[PDB]
Length: 108
Length: 159
Length: 175
Length: 127
Image (cartoon, rainbow over all chains, first blue to last red; front, side):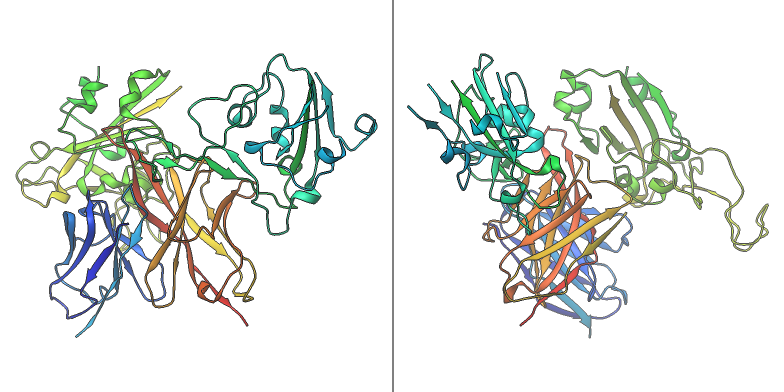
């Protein structure tokens, strides 16, 4: 029914650079989207929810915005601990829930 | 009587069977419960805790959505434990019971529909979702549960 | 008389939350920034009656609003306020930047920190007790690891929306 | 609160798989929470299996051919996953999580994403 698409598949950056990631949906969703981070060989953790609400305990450099069919995750200044994999997930009420393909970040 | 009591498989509680026809039952010690309050026999399987709901006047999930007896019932109810035939080492999930419905059943009423139950305010057009549940659920039987969670075979005669 | 609670001027600090004993006016308003209820629906509240209705109010930082919920964690939830795992009620909050924000800072509202044991649901700890420390006794700031157990917020006229003050009120129902 | 998992590491190429997850410092008997199971194939994305609610209701993923099963055990306060006739493509990591349910100002019912995760479990199909 509903499907996603993440881009780019892989990204390279350096400390202090700006990073942006885009999650696109097949049909409109009323801001029911979230972002996750996963380190190698560890359980994921939640960063953003409702496409714009920050999670408790996460740094303030993370931010997100958008609605309907386009969403973006932005990092103001990459730190050495911010290199990981990120996923976007939607929890609409009329269709089964699904995850994105994931994107990877590494040092240039 | 041998065919009804000694059959190989019983129907689910939500799809109980009907039968008509036109000593051992009284003396046998195998019948844990035997109380009597045109003949029509019945048969199904339920948990031991729900055996008390099959009686004139009781209320509950089984008595409201699956099987109902009239206040003026004239008959007898027979039930025995069948843990060594209806259980499995890995667990059995071949028995089902209804869990949601708009209204209660009438005496001797059967329901086989499998439509989607529309909970909440917004309607759903036959598509299950976060606010539209599937009305049937499954039982879980294992050889190590308490006596109250073991399967039981029930036969109710009506005259 | 909810106006006494939703329209008062003076509020209490989170470590010393205030309790009071007592609907369309509430859920028809659009000023409230957050409105979430657990166990019941706001529209059905007029169709039920209860023996007990408690109201609790205090002020916390905007970023910490998420901590006022069942099963949450954090400094406020661990040492200042705590909801049961089977709570039944509603949580209301709205921005209050026009108030409680003076040039140079207020430094009036406090919050507890460095407590040794987590609080139980629906309880308050007000007494100033011995300072959290390591293995050396402390009766002041004589220990380099010694610290006073309270802290003050720094609300100012200009700050990030996450650091602005928010007024919160919690309603509970029980019969 | 912490979640722990228990399961077998090896399984024959045609057998039944059984996993178990539990909680500490809380309780399952609450109408405020819901539980789910997630899995991840090696070097691939995540997949959602289904959800189970208080009162025994369930909700599964249509894409899968309803091979999985979720149920409680109130005698022990556990949650388990059942999958008979395992195959080669069933090697993956499995996770158990929890979420929250609440009512909106308009009266509708909404949900929050997962915020508690288990340590995961790895299973391999032998031969």
